[PDB]
Image (tube, coloured by chain):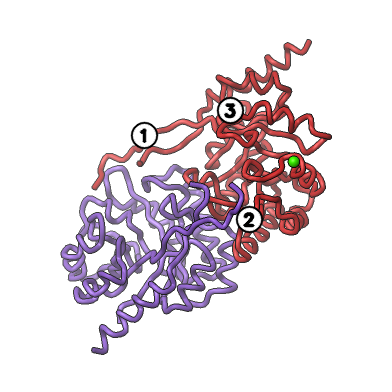
Chain colours: A purple, B red
Amino acid sequence: MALLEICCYSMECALTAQQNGADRVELCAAPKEGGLTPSLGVLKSVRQRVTIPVHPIIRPRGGDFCYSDGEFAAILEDVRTVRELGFPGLVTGVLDVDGNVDMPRMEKIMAAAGPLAVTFHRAFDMCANPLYTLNNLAELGIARVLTSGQKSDALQGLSKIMELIAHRDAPIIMAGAGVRAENLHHFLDAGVLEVHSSAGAWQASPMRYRDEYSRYIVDGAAVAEMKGIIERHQAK
Amino acid sequence: MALLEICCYSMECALTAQQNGADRVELCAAPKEGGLTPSLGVLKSVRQRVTIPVHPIIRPRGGDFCYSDGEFAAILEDVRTVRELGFPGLVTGVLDVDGNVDMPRMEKIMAAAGPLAVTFHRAFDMCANPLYTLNNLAELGIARVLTSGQKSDALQGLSKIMELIAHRDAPIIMAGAGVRAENLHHFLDAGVLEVHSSAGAWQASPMRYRNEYSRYIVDGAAVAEMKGIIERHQAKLE
Ligand SMILES: [Ca+2]
């Protein structure tokens, strides 16, 4: 059956995701930045508490993926860090100014990653040629790619995703961006092998003395609901 | 003369700040979150490339400072790690739901920090009872407090900042929020001994192809300008 990956911004989310049927978790920090590299403290906390596969994101800042040399140095050390801590995979991506995968720098990341399964994130949706990009990711040894079919949301890009899936010798295609219980069946029917969802919402701050009063948390019920949909899909 | 601290979101910013006269750097990640803990890669890079004092922020998420047990576990590990890596200080802060300093949690943070100079950040501006709080921070051994006088910007909170400074030797008061070359004199004349500035600027993305991308960087000239203002102000003192 299809693999369910949940985007998490805390160790507790990863646990809640796990307890509710998630098969994998992408670990990030800074939801308002779209996801940045977690601190060592969070990484260690996850390694001691979460058992399902966790792939931390390696992203020093928001915005584009054309990092400076300084930022890249940090990226390589963070890749080494995640590998040394024992995570089974990681999520990252570097592009050149023309919307192409930065092959030389991605090669250095792959070298540092060693045996870890590397996911190329939505930087993919910013690439000029999706097919040539898939070829490039395969050449690098990338395990999977997170994509919305190069559209605002994965559903709108589902027809493209089905085209991408038919491409031989390519990383696994994981649909992401707007995937939820309500539309999951569309991706399953399309034949998508893996799906990615934040399945979260902003929670109000418990502060009684006073956007600085809200937290981003995962909806465990939504995770459970999606896993259920996946289970029933291959049984009915 | 007053001390100039610059908020940096990268190793390159910190070095640029250092080369332009900054006395100290507060190191963070995620500017859209108001600053979160830097990744280990960034921390290690800074220890290798920057020589002026750098105080990394220890903050797992944006928003309030009433962390969960899980977030707090990470915070203590991050504090221990920053101490291990050799940083001279760090920036953090924890409050309870009523805006009081969470003493048990802060005590644990201080224990983990060892000899590091701990800055209690703008959590102070969200706390209740400023003087009582200053007393508690002194009890904890907090070295300094980053504050806007509990106002939207430090200049508005100038009078409050002065009252904090006058308060029976509380930790060092460092003015922050909207502090820049234009208004620096207000704080220096008020007797503020340490100032914190973003000295921020924006650089367009070099991206030529696209299917928001502006990078938040530091303005070296601005850092130098503020340092010059600080030097001259000190010169005025005979
Ligand atoms: Ca008071």
Mark pair 2, 1: CA separation: 40 Å
The answer to which of marks 2 and 3 sits earlier in the sequence is 2
Mark pair 2, 3: CA separation: 29 Å
Is A166 on the left or on the right of B201, as rendered?
A: left
**In the rendered structure, are the residues bearing label 1 and label 3 in contact, judged by CB atoms less than 8 Å apart?**
no
- At mark 1, the secondary structure is loop
- Residue A95: x and y in percent read 33, 49
- Residue A184: x and y in percent read 27, 72
Residue found at x 28% / y 75%:
A193
**Identity of the residue furthest to the front in this view:** A208
The answer to which of marks 1 and 3 sits earlier in the sequence is 3
Which amino acid is tagged 3? Val
Indicate the quadrant where residue A118 lies: bottom left
Quadrant location, the N terminus of chain A: bottom left
Q: Which chain carries label 2?
A: B
Quadrant location, the C terminus of chain A: bottom left
Q: Which chain carries label 3?
A: B
- At mark 3, the secondary structure is loop
Which amino acid is tagged 2? Val
Tell which of B101 and A124 is nearer to you: B101
Residue found at x 18% / y 68%:
A162
Which amino acid is tagged 1? Ala
Q: Mark 1 points at which residue?
A: B204
**Identity of the residue furthest to the bottom in this view:** A235
Mark pair 1, 3: CA separation: 24 Å
Residue found at x 51% / y 69%:
A87
Q: Mark 3 points at which residue?
A: B179
Are discs 2 and 3 both within one chain? yes
Disc number placed over residue B97 in the picture, else none: 2
- Foreground mark, 1 or 3, reads 3
